[PDB]
Every structure is written in structure tokens, then in C-alpha cells.
Image (cartoon, rainbow, N blue to C red; front, side):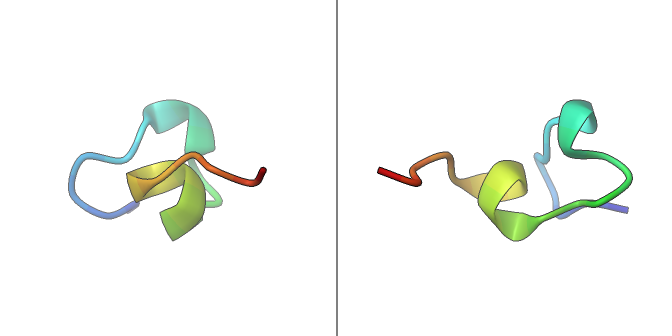
Length: 25
């Protein structure tokens, strides 16, 4: 799965960035 606390929406890619931290700007 996606790291602990990852938004299921980031699933199934489970990108730590979406998973644990949203900040691409």
C-alpha cells in the first residue's frame, strides 16, 4: 500500500508525495 496515512486517492500509485505531503509549488 501507500505509506501510513496516504490518501486512498493516491492509490494505487502510492506516491509518497501524495501520500504524505502535498506541495508541488
